[PDB]
Image 1: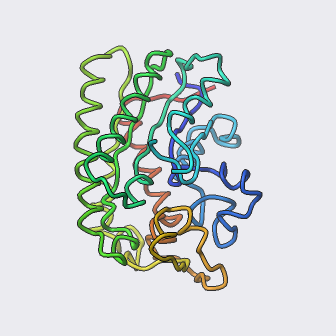
Image 2: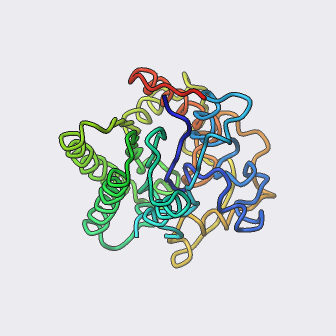
Length: 282
């Protein structure tokens, strides 16, 4: 069986890491929920909650930093380095490693399309190799949702570029994970097709509880130069203008999903791992 969960990610998986370093000033909470980039617990928190009730945060090693991505506030290599530094360079064999990364590199809307796609997928593949080289036996990799459906892309006309990033990224990542499966069959390889799961929720938004998928719960204002990052967008949130009732919103801010969308993600991920035969105890 497996003892704990180690998640490498960005603002979509951070459980308050940047919030602490920022001295509780970013993300401003409220309207954000205690440093999460949403109005509730993030998906990986709920998933660990379902496995270790009454004390999940003693089984969750969350190294995800807000604004993190592939070499950007923080790099995946450094999240992994942080774990390896604090474990004598040994990846625990009874730990589940989670890598959900890339969204922050693409949402920044860089100038080099293909080179960014290239360096993001190369950075992830490198991270899986390092973890596998240090003894990781259970690795979960998640692909990206259709970023063209974020209010950011819908406001700045980048639906084409963001959807293109999501599809091409998910295709390369699929081939990357297929390589590591045809190379390390001794390692349990787990995959989550976020792209398809989020498209199904979108096409059935009302059935999942959402009444609005284009607007935002909070409110923010950004401009050309400064707007070129997720963290500046989060820093430009106006707490006084955030809606009090956001039941129904799919997006809490210009890119981050609301608390309900994190719960749906965690429940689907739990069922997928239950389908795969992954057991947690101790």
